Every structure is written in structure tokens, then in C-alpha cells.
Amino acid sequence: SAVSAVFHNLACRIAPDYALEATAKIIATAKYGKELLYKQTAISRAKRAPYPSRMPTGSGNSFPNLNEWHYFP
Amino acid sequence: IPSFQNPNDWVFPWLTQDTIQIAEFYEVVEKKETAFIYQDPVTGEPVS
Image (cartoon, rainbow over all chains, first blue to last red):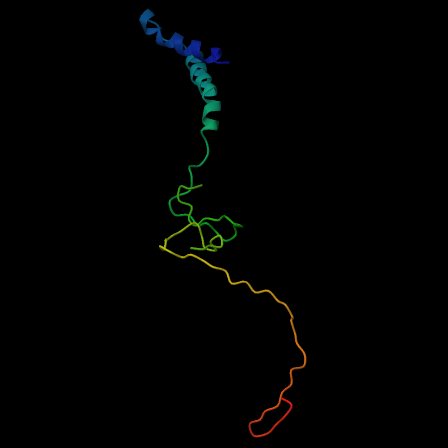
């Protein structure tokens, strides 16, 4: 699936060497293609960072056996 | 230098040098008794 992205981005970069510039379809597919390759990565990197230095340990919690959640959990 | 198992927290927002523990247990036995009647020679009154 990574094939369908790359050869558009590659054909754009070697184009000024040949005194050419890529057409509208090549630059559009190049950007949309590389975005779909990064699509799975940006989903997996999503999730909130651990709780701050000051966070309650709660009393709705049942037997946490700890006071303070610092960067402990 | 006895212990129980520590009743106290193990989180320890402070730590005292010695807090060593001993448990006083209470068990029940009825035992009871009977008789043992005496007199009082001081100013009368028998059947004490």
C-alpha cells in the first residue's frame, strides 16, 4: 500500500533536474498518499499523557491503598 | 521487640522511629463459683 504514495513524491523531486514540474494529479495523490501511510501512525500515537503531580486518590475508589497519584499510576 | 503485623499504613507520609506493637487479647471463660460463706467477727453479722 506504500507503493501508491511514494512514486508520485519521487517523480516530483527529480522533475526540476529534467526541467519539468509535476501536474496537478501527481502532487494531489502524493500528499493524499503519504497522509494515508501516516494515518495508522497518528491513530496509535493518540492517547492522553498521565495524570498531573496533584491528583486526588479519591474515596469513590475501593481500597487503592495509596495516597496521592503523582506520576505513580 | 514484638509486632502484630503493623496496624498502621505502609504509605508513610511520615515515619516514626519506633511504633512497635503488642496485642492484648480478651477471651471469655465463665468459670463461676459456689458456696464459701463465712461470718464477720467484727461487730456481728454472720452469713457474709
